[PDB]
Length: 129
Length: 198
Ligand SMILES: *[C@@H]1O[C@H](CO[C@@H]2O[C@@H](C)[C@@H](O)[C@@H](O)[C@@H]2O)[C@@H](O[C@@H]2O[C@H](CO)[C@@H](O)[C@H](O)[C@H]2NC(C)=O)[C@H](O)[C@H]1NC(C)=O
Ligand SMILES: *[C@@H]1O[C@H](CO)[C@@H](O)[C@H](O)[C@H]1NC(C)=O
Image (cartoon, rainbow over all chains, first blue to last red; front, side, top):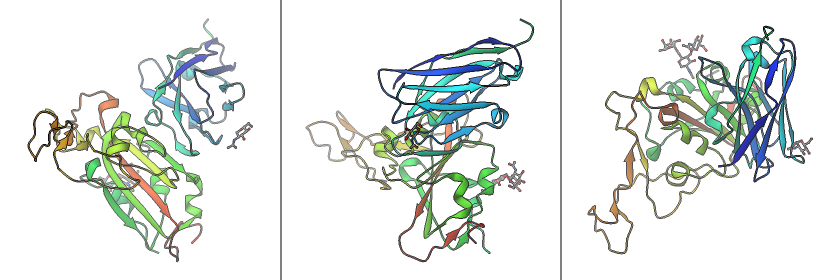
């Protein structure tokens, strides 16, 4: 297992943007695949976006045109840029890691593909603030 | 013109225990991966050494469909270079694996109120499994210095254990049906092609 810490959450107006950050602690993300998952209030945990050790990506349909996942192994960080945020995107966002020595290629990306999980960060998109 | 019989693999009524995992050789057919694409029930659908989008545009000598049932949190062990009770003692993929891994939740089929004790896994073995090796032995495991002579006792354990799937388990402990597709390119001709290379 490995230690994962998320950052970049907060409260933002619809149409605004956020940049989630997943920082590993005590290891490097070089051999690792990283995925982003979210769980909305009163709903189940859903896969949002994932990136392989070979830099191939997966994007859920509901975020396909708006989110962009990127990897920076030199800075030991994976980012999730989230543009054009909508209220349905309000959820707790979790980072997940899994060793990926060979290169994996996703068609879908689910929680069954990762063994290590972060504590999560809260994302809230409301104009009512 | 023949379509590959993916339905009889993925949609089989009964699935094998992981220790006695089932293998079906797929040959001389057109590999229509659309039915695999459009199944929105798959929790896991990933490939190694090949992009899952380019499957309809590739040809192979044989496609091996391996299927079994494990726990949710064990699905990740069905991957190159992974370790754990399932990968070490039940089903082992090679580090050079070329193929796809597909898994979906099967609590609605393989769980019983009071427990389904028909699905087993191997807990003990004197050495790890080689890739694609199967061990269906039922021999008493000698965990100590004293020989067992086939009698269960102190440091003499039965090598198989039961999952006992119940519907009320958390998703991590719930049953998941797994299908591993292996892509072989050994002896020509290629017999399994996508509709785009056909
Ligand atoms: C595995 O079966 C599903 C479901 O098939 C349905 O349920 C069966 C019990 C039987 O009554 C079938 O005739 C039903 O269609 C298949 O999913 C269907 O796929 C078709 C074509 O892709 C699609 O039009 C339907 O909407 C799907 N239905 C559902 C409920 O998902 C699936 O294709 C089968 N898998 C394979 C590999 O053949
Ligand atoms: C992934 O991206 C990084 C940064 O662009 C690059 O250095 C690395 O070689 C890439 N890896 C692969 C397998 O393409």
